[PDB]
Length: 202
Length: 206
Image 1 (tube, one colour):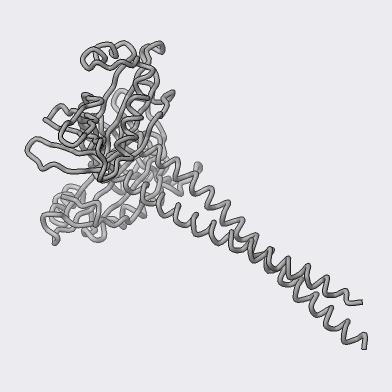
Image 2 (cartoon, rainbow over the protein chains, first blue to last red):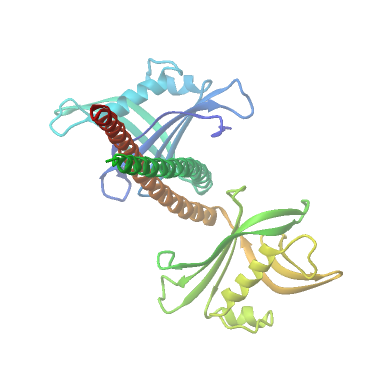
């Protein structure tokens, strides 16, 4: 399937989403959106796009979408999506960018909506002009399950563990440099105090 | 089991001899973490939990969990002289022995994890030439999808946190480094200016 190793992040930012769940109350949450593009393990010629909706506050919350260069004609059909596969992530980004920048008094107002109906969920980005609500994109996401959330958290962990390692390396290098500057400052202060004595010389 | 009020008593990699049914024997370095706390349901019930994981296989997990109550069965089915409070200490010293063991040693302390599928047995053995004498033998359950999920979410928030702290120190360190360079440059300026004031004043007084 999809190899999160050879993957490329195109977008990875929190977006203000209106989450609507089945027997729970409507809530405005800030959810993380990551748009990934790569290939299939089985066939290195099959391009795939992956989208993840997660929360930094709920580490178990996850919603996923996955479409190959092939199956894109199915998704494109029924939706009316004018754009091709290569163009698709760009259409998604600009729309999520509009939602990010939306301000209270706005009209037309761009709003992201995630409707959770048990084992399936629908993500839409809508343009709200007073009464009328016009959708720019409507997508089909699958929530959970235990096996998928498990793999995601293992990916996230190795990822954070890695950026942690890099931070540690810079801190070492920075601390080493700071220590060298103090030695140089002390030597300069010594030269300065010695020159002052050499000034007397009376 | 309260993971909020929990306490880590041990947390280190130990060299373990992993034996699996249908696979070849392997010497791996596995992470051991010993925690003690209480039950969510009853704040009066003391519990001990031990996790065996790998930094190389993020899905590998084997767990052991015993409450102050359940200890007596574990104690009888073993001959363990020590009480519940004393038990983690017995485990630690044995894990230290395995950690410090060197190749040519005899008596040599060795950690062994046997996987039969659905169940796994962890033992710490003393090897004096031929004879192998076990000091501890424990029953571990390999983690399922739901248990591995919770573990990785715990690990992630934990690393995400120590990552934040590292970032803060790097900011503070970088700020200090930048200030030292400014101080060094100012000192070098003062030094060059004094030199001109000296040179001139000595030429002038002639």
